[PDB]
Image: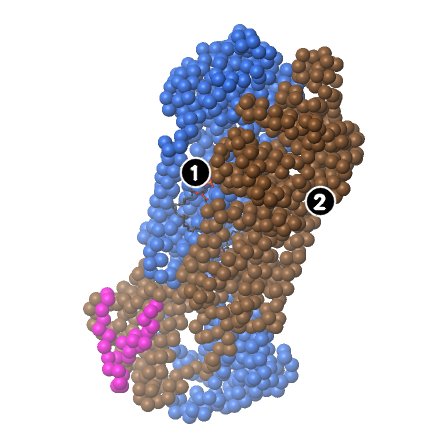
Chain colours: A brown, B blue
Amino acid sequence: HAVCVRHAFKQYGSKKNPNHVLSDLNMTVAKGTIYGLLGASGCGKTTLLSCIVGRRRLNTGEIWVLGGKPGTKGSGVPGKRVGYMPQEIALYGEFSIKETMMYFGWIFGMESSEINERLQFLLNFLDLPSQNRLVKNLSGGQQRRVSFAVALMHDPELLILDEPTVGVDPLLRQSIWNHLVQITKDGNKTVIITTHYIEEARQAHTIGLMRSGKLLAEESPHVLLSMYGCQSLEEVFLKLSSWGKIKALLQKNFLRMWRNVGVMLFIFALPVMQVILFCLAIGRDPTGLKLAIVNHEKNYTNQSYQECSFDYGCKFSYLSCRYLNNLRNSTILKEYYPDPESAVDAVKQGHAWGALYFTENFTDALVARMALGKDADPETLDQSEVRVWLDMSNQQIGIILQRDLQLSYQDFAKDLLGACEQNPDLAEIPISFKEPIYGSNKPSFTDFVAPGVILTIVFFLAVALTSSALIIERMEGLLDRSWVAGVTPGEILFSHVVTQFVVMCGQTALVLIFMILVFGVQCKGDIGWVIVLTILQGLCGMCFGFVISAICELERNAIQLALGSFYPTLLLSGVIWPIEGMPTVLRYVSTFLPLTLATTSLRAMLTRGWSIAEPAVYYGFLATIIWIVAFLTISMLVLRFK
Amino acid sequence: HAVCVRHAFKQYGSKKNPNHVLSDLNMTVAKGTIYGLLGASGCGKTTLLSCIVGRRRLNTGEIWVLGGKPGTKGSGVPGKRVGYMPQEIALYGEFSIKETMMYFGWIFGMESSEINERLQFLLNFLDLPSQNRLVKNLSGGQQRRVSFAVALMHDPELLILDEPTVGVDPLLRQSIWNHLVQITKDGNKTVIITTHYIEEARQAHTIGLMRSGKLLAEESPHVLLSMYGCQSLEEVFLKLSSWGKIKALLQKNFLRMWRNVGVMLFIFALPVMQVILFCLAIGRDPTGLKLAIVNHEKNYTNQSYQECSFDYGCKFSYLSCRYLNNLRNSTILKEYYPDPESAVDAVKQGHAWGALYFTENFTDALVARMALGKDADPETLDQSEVRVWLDMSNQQIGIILQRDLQLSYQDFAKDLLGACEQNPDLAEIPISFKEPIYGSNKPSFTDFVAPGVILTIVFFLAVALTSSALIIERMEGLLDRSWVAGVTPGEILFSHVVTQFVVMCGQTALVLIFMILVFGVQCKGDIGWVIVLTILQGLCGMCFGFVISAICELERNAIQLALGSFYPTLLLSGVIWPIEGMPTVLRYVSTFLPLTLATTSLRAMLTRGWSIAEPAVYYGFLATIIWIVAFLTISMLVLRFK
Ligand SMILES: CCCCCCCCCCCCCCCCCC(=O)N[C@@H](CO)[C@H](O)/C=C/CCCCCCCCCCCCCNc1ccc([N+](=O)[O-])c2nonc12
Ligand SMILES: CC/C=C\C/C=C/C/C=C/C/C=C\C/C=C\CCCCOC[C@H](COP(=O)(O)OCCN)OC(=O)CCCCCCCCCCCCCCCCC
Ligand SMILES: CC/C=C\C/C=C/C/C=C/C/C=C\C/C=C\CCCCOC[C@H](COP(=O)(O)OCCN)OC(=O)CCCCCCCCCCCCCCCCC
C-alpha cells in the first residue's frame, strides 16, 4: 500500500472558531496505480497532502505511507523516495534551469553525470527553452513546467502532483498523461494527483471525491459511472447527499546575493559611503567664522584692509595690532568696520559672528594698567578692555570663539613679558593643567562618535538581512519544498549563520579600514579585541532577526518593527551624546539595552588603550553574550506556541 | 453587437526580441448571449480582456465595445455600463462585506437605500456568511464569491468574468450558471466568461477557442461538436493543424489605517516617543562627574569627608577649602585621597575624571603671590598653583571640567577682594564679553538639534507612508479594478494628497506641542511660519514617495531606495553638527540637498526670531518649493518611458 489513512481527524483554530477540516477520513492508495483526488475547495486536499508528506500532524487517526509513519525514520517519506510538486511555484528566481536542476540533484545525492542526462531528457520532453534562461525571465506556464520537471528528476517511487496541468497546451497535456501512464504501469511507482478539474482525471485508476472533510466515494472511474448511471463524472459528483546538502545550500545562499545588484549595493556600498561621509562632516572644527573688527587706533581703509603694523621688539607701540597678530588664522576671518554701531549691525544680520571694538586709547590704558597693578583707577580699567559682543545662538561655534579669543590673549601676554626679559610664568592663572592622563589637550568629537557608528552599522545591517531573507523565503514555500526534499531544519539554520558570518566579516574589514587607516581615527588598544567585539555585535544583531521573522509574516510588518526599535535605542545607548546627560532613573534603564555597554567598551579600547582585564571593557563582552542567549530563547519560545 | 475586434495586432518587446502576444484577431460578441473564451495560457486572453475594458491600447486594428472605442467618448465602457471581475482577488482587506458593497455602490452613484436590497439578494443567493465578517477573515473560496457579488451588484449590461468558478462547490456552480443564463434571456445583457477549464463552458451560447494569439474557431458548442463529429470539446480543441467618488475614496483611505493598529502606532506614536527620548537624553550637560581632591592642608578622615572650614571675613585662613566652596555643586562630585600619586591612580582607572592636589604651602604662597605682583620669585609661583591632571579622552566632558574649574577661580578671586573693600573689576582679563546679541551665555546643544529633528521626522514619515500605500494598491490589482469603475486617476491622486495632508498636520501638532509646550524648547520667532515650513517639508516628502513608487515595483526595493537616501542626507544637512565644519567643496554640494536650507531657515526662526524678510529665512521656503516641482517632474518622466 502506497498510503493508508485510517480514521483521520484534524482541527484548526481555537475553540471559539473550530474548523473540522478532516473528520473520520479513510483513504487507501495501492502500488502501481494513479489515484486522482477531486475536491470542491482547495484546502482539504492540500491539508491531506501536507499530512501525508509529514509537514503537519493528525489530531486523531493513523497514517502509513511507503511503509511507516510520516517523518519517523521508519520510512523515507521526506527524502529521495518522494516527489513533491507544490500548488504554488516554489522555485528560486535568479536561477537558470540548469542551476535549479543541479541544486536539487545535489540535495537528493545524485551525481553530476546523471543530472545532465535527466536535464536533457526533461528539456526535450517538456518543451522548454534553453537551460541558461533564468527562471525569473520565464512566463507562468514555463515556470510551472520547470516546477514539474523538478519533481521528476530523481525518479521517486511516489509522486505527489498538485494540479500538474492547469493551463498546459493540450498536446503537452496528452504527452504528460501518456508519460505518467508509462511510468506507473506494471511497476512500483505511484502517482497522487490533486486537481479542481473534474474531467481530466478519467485516466486515474482510482478516483476519490472529497466533500465536508471526507470521501463521498472511492472507486474506478467507469465503475462509478456505471454504478451511479451517469453520462459524465460531474453528474456523479453532482449528488445532493550531510555535507552534500550544506555545500548545495552554501552555493545557493551566496548566489542569491550575487545576482541582486541592489542587495550588494545596500550591504557593501552603503557602509563604505556612510563611513566616508561621517568622517568628513561630523566632529570637525568650524573653520570659516568671520568677525567684525573696529580698531580705532588705525585709519579705516576698506572692509578687507587695515594695515595692522607695529614694532615687534618693545616700547608697546600699538598693542591692538599686536593682539590681532596672535589670533588663530584657520578659523577666524577678519573684517573691518568704522563704527561699533556698524559692526553690531553686521552681527544682527548674517555677516559676522561677533564684534571687537578696540578703543582709540587702548595702548596707553593697557600699559598704565600692567605698570600700575592692584590699584588701577576705574578709568583705566574701562579704557583698557576689549569689548566682545558674540552671537551665542550656536553652542559649538560660541564655544570656539570664546576659547580662541581668550587663548590668544595668553599668547599675547606671554609675548609682552619675555620681550622685556621677564619670565612668562607670571601670566598664568593658579589653576594649572598638567599633561593629560588620557587623550590630549585638543580632543575631537568624531573620535567620540566613531565607536558608536561602527557598532550601529554592523548590528542593524544584520537585522535587515536576516529578517528579509527568512521571511521572503518562508512565504513562497521555498522552505517547505526543501524540507520534503530531506533538508533538516538544523542544516537550514547552519548555512544561514555561515553565510551571514562571512558577510559581516567583509563589512568589518571595510568599516575598520576606512575609519582607521584612511581617515586616521586612533586605535590605542588591541586591534584583535576590536575585531572580536564588532563581530559579536553582528551575531547579536542576527539573532534579533530570528525574533522578528518568527513574529512577523509580512515584509511591511518586519520593517516597522525593525525601524521601531532602531530609533529608540540610538538615542539611549550614548552614541551621539555622553551617557552622563540623562537623569539617574533613565541612566539605569539604558545600561541594559543591547548596545550601551558595548559602545562604552569599544570607546575605552580606542581612546584609552585599555585591555580585556579592565571591568569597563569586559562588561561589553558579557552584555552581548547575554543578549545573544536572550534573543535565542525568545525566538524559540515564540515558535513553541505559534 | 456588443464587442467587435478586427485585426487586433499587439506586440511586447523593444524591437529586438519581440513577443507576438496578439496576431490577426477577429472576434464578434452578439448581444444577449453567453460567450466563452477558452485559451490555453492565461496571458493572451487577459491581454484581450484588458484591451476590451480599456486599460491598454493596440498597435493595429479596431476595437469597438458597446458603441465606441474604449476609454474615449461615445461609450461608457469604463464606468457603470460594464462589470469586471479580475483574475486575482482585488478586494480590500480590513473591510466588512457590507462596507465593500457600500463603497463600490457609491463609486457607481447608486443610492444607499437600494444597495441594501442588492446586498441581501446576493448574500442569500451566493451562500455567504453574515455581512459583518471582515474580508480577511473569510476563507479563500469565499473571497472569490464576494468578488463575484461585487461584479454583479450594480446590474451592468456587459459582464466580463475572469474564471468565476475555480474552487466552487458544484451545487453552487449549477446555480451560478442558471443565473447567468437567466439574466441574459432575450435581453440586453451579455457575458464574456474566460476559463482554462474547457468542460465547464458548454452552457455558453458561443465559444471561441484561442491559440497562438488568434481564434481557431468561433461557433456554437453543439455546431462545433457536430461539424467535427467529436464527442466532447476536449477532442475538438485537439487541433494539431465627481463628489461621491471622492467622498467614497476618502472613507476608504481613513478606514484602511484606522483598522491597522501597527500603522497607527508607527506614524502617530513613534514620532511622539522619539521626541520625548531626544529631549531627555541628547543635548543636556553632564552632571555626575567625580573629582579626586588631594588637600594637604587638612587631615584625612574618609574618602567622602574632609571637614573643610575657614573664616568668611578676611585674614585668609586656608584658601584651599575656600576655593572648593565656589566649585559648582551640580556637575562635580568631590572625593578625597591621601596622596598626590594615589589620586592619579583613581584617574587611570574609571574612579575619577581628574585630580586637584592643593599643596601644604598653598595658603601662604597664594597670599604672597597676589600681594607681590610682577616680582614673585619662581619658587612662589610653583607653590601657589593648583595642579590638575584631567582625563581628556571625552571631548564634551573635558569642556565642562575645564570650564567649571576656571570659572570657579573667578568667583573665588572676585570674593577675596570685595570682602577686603577692593574693586572686583581688578580680577578680570581685558577680553570682556558683553551681553550676547543673540542667545544667552549658557547655550544648549539640544536647541541646536531640535530644529533639525522636527523636519527629519516629518519628511521621512511621509516617504514611508506614500511609497507603501501606492505600491500595495498597484501590485494587488486594486488600482486597476477601480479604474474600470470610473474613478479617474485625477480623483485617486487628489484624494491621496488630502489624506496625507491631514495626517502630516496631526503629526506636526503632536511634535510641536511635545517640543515647545513640554520640555520648553525656546521659540523666539513667529509660530505661524514655523507651522507653514514644517508642513511644506511634509509635502516635499510625499512627492519623493511618488518618485520611489513610480520607479520600484516590489516592496523590498522601495525600502532600500528610501533608506539608501535617508542616511546620506542626514549626514550632509547639518542636523547633528554645524555645517561650518564640512570642507568647502562638500559644503557647496550640501546646500542643494532637500533638507539643508530648510533646517537652516527653521533654526534662525527658533533661536534668533528672524522674520520672513531675512534672506536666510525665505531661502528655506524657496528650496522646498523648487524640490517639490523637481520631484513632480521626475515622477512624470519616469512614468512616460516605463
Ligand atoms: C532597518 C534597520 C536598520 C537599517 C540599516 C541601518 C544602517 C546603519 C545605521 C546607520 C547609523 C549611522 C549614523 C547615525 C547618526 C544619525 C543621527 C540620528 O540618529 N538623528 C536622529 C535624531 O537625532 C534622527 O534625526 C531622528 C530620526 C527618525 C526619523 C523617522 C524616519 C522614519 C522612516 C525612515 C525612512 C522610511 C523607511 C521606509 C519604511 C516604510 N515602512 C512602512 C511600510 C508599510 C506601511 N504600510 O503597511 O502602509 C507603512 N506605513 O507607515 N510606514 C510603513
Ligand atoms: C533592540 C531590541 C529591544 C528590545 C529587545 C526585546 C523585547 C522582545 C521583543 C519584543 C517586541 C514586542 C512586542 C511585539 C508584539 C506583538 C506583534 C505581533 C502580534 C500582532 O501584531 C501584528 C503585527 C505582526 O502580525 P502579522 O503576522 O504580520 O499580521 C498577520 C499577517 N497575515 O505586528 C506589528 O506589526 C507591530 C507593529 C510595531 C509598530 C512599531 C512602532 C511602535 C511605537 C511604540 C509602541 C507603543 C505601544 C502602545 C501599546 C498600545 C496597545 C494597543
Ligand atoms: C533625498 C533626495 C536624494 C537625492 C535627490 C535625487 C534625484 C534623483 C533620485 C534619484 C534616485 C533614483 C533612481 C536610481 C536608479 C536606478 C534604480 C532603479 C532602476 C533599476 O533598479 C532595479 C530596482 C527596481 O526594480 P524592482 O521594482 O525592485 O524589481 C521589479 C522586478 N520586475 O531598483 C532597486 O533595486 C533599488 C535598490 C537601491 C539600492 C540602494 C543603494 C544605496 C547606495 C548606493 C551607492 C552608490 C551607487 C553607485 C551605482 C553603481 C551602479 C552599478
In this figure, which residue is indicated by the disc labeled 1?
B550
Determine whether, in the image, residue A533 is placed left or right of residue B71: right
Q: Is mark 2 on a helix, strand or loop?
A: helix
**For the point 57% across and 43% down, which residue is it?**
A113
**For the point 54% across and 66% down, which residue is it?**
A530
Determine whether, in the image, residue B244 is placed left or right of residue A80: left
**For the point 36% across and 58% down, which residue is it?**
B586
Quarter holding the C terminus of chain A is: top right
Q: Is residue B384 above or below residue A273?
A: below
Q: Is residue A25 visible?
A: yes
Q: Is residue B158 visible?
A: no
| Figure quadrant of residue B164 | top right
Q: Residue B614 carries which label?
A: none
Q: Please determine if labels 2 and 1 lie on a single subunit.
A: no
Q: What element carries label 1?
A: helix
| Figure quadrant of residue B541 | top left
Magenta span of residues: A303-331
Please name the amino acid that badge 2 sits on. Phe
Answer yes or no: do the residues labelled 2 and 1 have beta carbons within 8 Å? no
Q: Which of A522 and A526 is in front in this view?
A: A526
Magenta stretch: residue A324 in it? yes
Q: Does the residue labelled 1 lie within 8 Å of ligand 3?
A: no
In this figure, which residue is indicated by the disc labeled 2?
A641
